[PDB]
Amino acid sequence: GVVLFYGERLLVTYDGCKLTLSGSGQQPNGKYSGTAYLTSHRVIFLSKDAALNSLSMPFVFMARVAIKAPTFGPNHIEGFVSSQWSGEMPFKLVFNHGGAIEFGKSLLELGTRASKLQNSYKTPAAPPLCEIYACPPPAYTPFVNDPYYNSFMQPHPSFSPPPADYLYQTNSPPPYPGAVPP
């Protein structure tokens, strides 16, 4: 399952994604196939097979994110996660069914917005009793229904249904900012 923070919105589900972590030294390094989730706050990747079952890349720790197109091959997304390990770990997201440009354009706009709040964000007070429960449907409603997200994200037919029966929410707020209405 996927556990969203309180105040986090699930925006895009992409089944059939390949994530490559290309760290050196002690940084993470491996290849993973599965589903990528684009939220207001992070990319979540769930390995479908597994040295790692789940990983989260908060926008505020991503750097130099770009939609890449090699001279002959398909569009993909590249970037880094910044500083167990320290320094700059490269990552690459490849999409099996197209929609890399649409996913990446959305990621760039979300990440730009979230990163501008990095210095001012203070995690809200959290309930001492931490709860995980079935995710409220509003947290994963199609983003086209929300003018805040619909104004800068484009749909794509390769985007997949949100896995409602696998979505949970915690009452804990996210420890980093996201792209949300002010």
Image: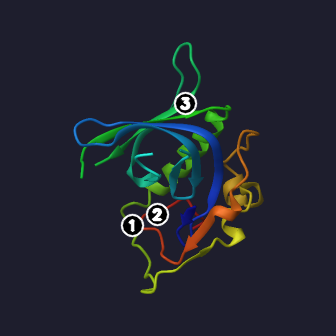
The mark that comes first in sequence, 2 or 3, is: 3
Residue 177 image label: 2
Report the Cα–Cα distance between label 1 and label 3.
32 Å
> Looking at the image, which is closer to me, 179 or 165?
165
For residue 169, side relative to residue 161 (left or right): left
Which residue is situated farthest in the top direction here?
72
Task: Say which residue appears at 68% left-offset and 32% top-offset.
Answer: 97
For residue 85, side relative to residue 103 (left or right): left
Task: Say which residue appears at 57% left-offset and 58% top-offset.
Answer: 40
**What percent of the width, then of the height, locates residue 158?**
72, 39
Amino acid found under the numbered disc labelled 1 = Ser
Name the element at disc 1. Answer: loop
Residue 76 image label: 3
Task: Say which residue appears at 47% left-offset and 81% top-offset.
Answer: 130
Q: Mark 1 points at which residue?
A: 120
The mark that comes first in sequence, 1 or 3, is: 3
Which quarter of the rendered picture does the C terminus lie within?
bottom right
Amino acid found under the numbered disc labelled 2 = Pro
Name the element at disc 2. Answer: loop
Which image quarter: residue 176? bottom left
> Looking at the image, which is closer to me, 137 or 32?
32
Q: In the rendered image of this protein, does residue 127 appear above or below residue 3?
A: below
Q: In the rendered image of this protein, does residue 123 appear above or below residue 90?
A: below
Tag 1 near tag 3, CB within 8 Å: no
**What percent of the width, then of the height, locates residue 156?**
73, 40
